[PDB]
Amino acid sequence: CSLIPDYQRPEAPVAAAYPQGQAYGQNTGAAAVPAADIGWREFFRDPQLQQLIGVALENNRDLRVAALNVEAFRAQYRIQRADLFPRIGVDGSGTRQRLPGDLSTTGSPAISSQYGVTLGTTAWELDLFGRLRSLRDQALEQYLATEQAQRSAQTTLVASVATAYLTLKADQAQLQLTKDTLGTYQKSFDLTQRSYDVGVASALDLRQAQTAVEGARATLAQYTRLVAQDQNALVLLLGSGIPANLPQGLGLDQTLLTEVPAGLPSDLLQRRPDILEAEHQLMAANASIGAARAAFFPSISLTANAGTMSRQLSGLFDAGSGSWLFQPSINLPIFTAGSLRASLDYAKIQKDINVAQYEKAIQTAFQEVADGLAARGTFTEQLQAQRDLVKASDEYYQLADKRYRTGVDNYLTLLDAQRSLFTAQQQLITDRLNQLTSEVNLYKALGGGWNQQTVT
Amino acid sequence: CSLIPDYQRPEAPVAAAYPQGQAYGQNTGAAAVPAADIGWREFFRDPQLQQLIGVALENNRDLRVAALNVEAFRAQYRIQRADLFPRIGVDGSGTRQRLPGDLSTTGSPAISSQYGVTLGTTAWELDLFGRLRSLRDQALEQYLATEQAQRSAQTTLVASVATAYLTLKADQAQLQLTKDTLGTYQKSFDLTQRSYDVGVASALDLRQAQTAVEGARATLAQYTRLVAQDQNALVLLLGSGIPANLPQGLGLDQTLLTEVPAGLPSDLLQRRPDILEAEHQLMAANASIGAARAAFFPSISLTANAGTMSRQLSGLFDAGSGSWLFQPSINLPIFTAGSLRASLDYAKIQKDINVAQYEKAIQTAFQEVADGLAARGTFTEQLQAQRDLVKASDEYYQLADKRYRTGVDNYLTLLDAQRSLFTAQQQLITDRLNQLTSEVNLYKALGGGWNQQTVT
Amino acid sequence: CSLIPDYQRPEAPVAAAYPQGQAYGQNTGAAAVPAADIGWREFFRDPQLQQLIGVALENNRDLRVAALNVEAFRAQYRIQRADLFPRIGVDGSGTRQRLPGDLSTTGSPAISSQYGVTLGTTAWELDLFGRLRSLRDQALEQYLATEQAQRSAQTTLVASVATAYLTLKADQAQLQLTKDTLGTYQKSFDLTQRSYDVGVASALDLRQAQTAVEGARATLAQYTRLVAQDQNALVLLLGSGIPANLPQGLGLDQTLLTEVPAGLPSDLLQRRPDILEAEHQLMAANASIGAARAAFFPSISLTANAGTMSRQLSGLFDAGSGSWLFQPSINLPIFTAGSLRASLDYAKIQKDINVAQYEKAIQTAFQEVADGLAARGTFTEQLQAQRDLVKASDEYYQLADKRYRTGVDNYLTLLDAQRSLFTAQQQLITDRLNQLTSEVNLYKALGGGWNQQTVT
């Protein structure tokens, strides 16, 4: 017997379609090559990023823990596996008691005694109704779950490494942008000083100019700090130092990511690792019901022997001192005070809990992918507008500087255009960061980067 | 015996009063109907929200896990409960050994053997000094704790659902506000273009105008994204789709929430579920001391029988083969190497730990409610000022546009007034969101929304 | 025997040096007095903070849990310790069975029986190959780990208390700054009203002025809220009320912190408590290998007696009813179905897992200190620039107000200078907060504030 219930994978409690509305492109339906199947070496066009990910998979201690845990759980399966087979040792026993007259063989106070090197099993449980086999398959599903948890952990690592790298690249651009800008404010301030010296620019003009310089200096210090803290974050996720002979990277203006396709909600159940994870736990919960069911049914047990017994140690390995034992022990529970029913309620409840966690994982997955698509339907429009804003801000700036130098107009307008230009450029860098990050996370949420190369 | 210590609920280590200072309204003292007692159907005036909460309580997988866990722990109580009663089975034994001559009945190598279908108990522990009863009441308090954890989980769910909904409603307003505003910037830009074509507005004016348009376009894309991600967040907390025939909602200008009263700090100990939770764990810790104390005291045990024994299987259900057994086993420990004292130290330490966690929960609760009241004493002033800022910003805007069109004044002033108006309106929406959120959280922290209707 | 493997502390998988680059001061190399050794009473120059920390160490429930847990784990060690010594009780047994004729002494259905108050041990495991001693030293390392976790918890508490206090002091300054500023906007608005009444200032001027007033009012309400919520946060971390007779504090302009030295990366392995923590867990993992190894080797066991036995209860404490028992039981496993190998794989895997967690803790520590130094190499430049920005902003303001009052220039410039001044001052307060916080955290990450006074 196996008393394990049949397993029916529960109904995905999400909509058949990903959402629609103003924020999303049209649903692309079924995907020839699911996003879960696209290798990260392919998804990440930047060759420098690729190597970094590689380093991280080799060296990152959290992922290393996740792989070790797969082994831990296999070892656990191997323990339960062994449990269906008899433990056989060499049991060298030896009683030597003094009894009183009213209990002795003689009738006066005697000293009886025995000895016995044997070979056999004690209390071997014979798995007729399948308590152990159930516990075993429960351990197997848990191993399988832990296998999925590793893949999950990897996809999380890939996403974090790419993000840490992109964040670095962003802040490096902010810093460089700030460098150039400070140079320009210093230049403008010097021109304005020569003008003030010569009688033309006002003290107010000069203070305004100074104001732009100092604000830019402060931002410079900030981004210098952020760039460095980004490297520290990346080195941590790598689990070792930044390699010394990287290929050249790609700038954020270039194309960094492969378009990965939406797929259908239903692909998550076959392809996202933490959903499979949760499913395995459910199947483990389900196997544990078997165990609790078997506790009702009769329970075979067995001690078995062969060896040499004697009255004194000296007669042990002497001819015809041979000994053996054979002893079955069938047991059928009849009255628990509900204990066995309660243990069975417990196991079913545990299954129900895992149904619900499995549903949850599905729901979470939907939400994250939906959000990914909300980003994908909106960031192209946003960057396009933000780029227009930079361009116009820049035209605004060119005019305002000219109108100021020429005496035609005031410093306040120049100051206004300078701020507008600098904040738009910073913001443009951030928007591009956020849009890259949304796709990275979308790739992770579809089923991510477990594969190095695309699987056909 | 029960060797469980008397339980004295520890002293609430918080101030008798909620704080005072510039940030708070006067303490309202004792509350006729404690906030914990106000049903969410009453606290939440918005009928659309009400249904959404309802959907969430039916469908949310995390709360479903919490309820299942209550059952899990009841099942656990039922196990310990059963443990004070004898396990009675049908134990069909059967030895068959070969002994040597110096051990046999004969004096030459013999094969002895027995068989015996019986009915009785093995090693039934008789609970004189109460080890089991203690373990049992420990399981009962844990069940009670888990009951409180569900209520806690519900109050967390109510708070999150209301928040997710309000956040949606806020972003919907931001989006609509942005829509209108873009329309106005487009309109202004077109007017400024006709003016430029006709010789009047300057190129600078035109660039400035353009600048407002593009910034507004970018914000539009952003809020379109946020509105959608908000729906995704709400659908997740609901644990199913947004229903298809909702009542009409209420706008954020309208009255959304019932005024809930402060109460006294002391109400938290009778009414906040995670404080009661922590208390039950403390009472469970306390019950476990009983268990460890009993390990010192003597320990009755019992095997009992009735059945049919025989020398061969064939004589089992034959007349007068009747058999029975009765066997007590009192045991008083005398020398542990401190083990039993250590086990008792452990249990007391575990109680102390739970005293401290119970105190903590109280302290956390105080802090959260205090913060709630800091919000309640300040958000009315803040919104009032922010509304004034909108009004004045709007007057500022009307004038600046007029002065610009009329040639009386420059585009920079118009641009300044346009930004001031738009950021104040956005900020006003956010402030109202934050103030609603503070009360929602305050309601949760007082003891929340476990009840559907107000309890009298 | 101890079958525990030799322990080699793993190689610190971080760079020999802390990072260099634009963000960092030169590496200061080895430190005469490591930062871990500087007492918090010394590191924190503010006497009011010092007392607050003191209060927190006395009263904070989380740290109290951490200390109790050290005791819990010592108790656990004491349990395993006791396990190498024999449990000796008083075992008052007593069988009374009815057998059938074919099993009885007589040959017809008899009722045999025995009784026996004794004193001795049951199944005392004799630790030849060291299963128990291993389990014991595993419990000792776990105790040691938990000891380190307390220190860690303290250093976290010190850092949080200082931070909560600084955050309070910051917001108090923001609030005061806002108070003064509002006073100035009200003053300016009144002057502008008298000007408008008298025919000179324009309606636009007046609206602009109003705008500054209302924005300042809203900020006032906000910081009033934040100041209070900060106190609530501090009171929580203290685990009791704010004392009633504090020394006077220090303002944020003053010197608050001792310069703590970098040290070398290598100091973290001897001095950061959670790294030592992780090491102890590793040494515990390592000790558990011993246990699993011993399961292969033979296994001595022993029951021993002295007492009084009899055929009837009435003969127990009668002369020459003396009884005793002596019974060894050596056992060597021969066939497991790989179970014992699997259990040994498991224990080694568990060691490997702890190698990796130990490495991780080191890596995390490096990252946090590196970040600390990135702050230390950049915040002096940043504050210096931000201070310049305040100064210039203030000059800008003085001029703009003068040029406005005098009819020489417009309100927009005044408005611009007013915003620039107020946001720079707020920002300056925040930067100073962040820079203080970085050093506080840097001190914590080096090895923190376990010591009250500097250790020589």
Image (tube, coloured by chain):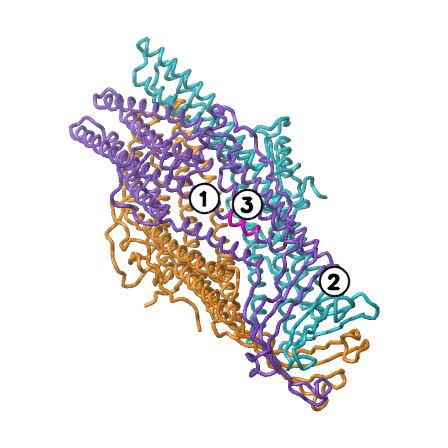
Chain colours: A cyan, B orange, C purple
Residue C280: mark in rendering: 3
| Rendered location of residue A106, percent (x, y) | 70, 80
Amino acid identity at mark 2: Val
For residue B386, say whether it is visible.
yes
Q: Are the numbered discs 2 and 1 placed on the same chain, yes or no?
A: no
> Residue drawn 64% across and 31% down?
A47
Q: Residue furthest left?
A: C198
For residue B193, say whether it is visible.
no
Amino acid identity at mark 3: His
Q: Quadrant of the C terminus of chain B?
A: bottom left
Q: Residues within 10 Å of mark 3 (few under 14, many from 20)?
A: many
Viewer-proximal residue among B96 and C308: C308
Q: CA distance from mark 2 to mark 3?
A: 37 Å
The chain to which mark 3 is attached is C
Amino acid identity at mark 1: Arg
Q: Which residue is mark 2?
A: A90
> Residue drawn 42% across and 46% down?
B172
Depicted C407 relative to depicted C39: above or below:
above
The chain to which mark 1 is attached is C
| Rendered location of residue B202, percent (x, y) | 38, 22
User: Which span of residues is magenta-colored?
Assistant: C137-144
Q: Looking at the rendering, which quadrant does residue A407 occupy?
A: top left
> Residue drawn 59% across and 63% down?
A351
| Rendered location of residue B91, percent (x, y) | 66, 78
The chain to which mark 2 is attached is A
Q: Looking at the rendering, which quadrant does residue C317 occupy?
A: bottom right
Q: Which residue is mark 1?
A: C151
Q: Residues within 10 Å of mark 1 (few under 14, many from 20)?
A: many
Viewer-proximal residue among A191 and B404: A191
| Rendered location of residue A23, percent (x, y) | 51, 44
Q: Is residue C139 magenta?
A: yes
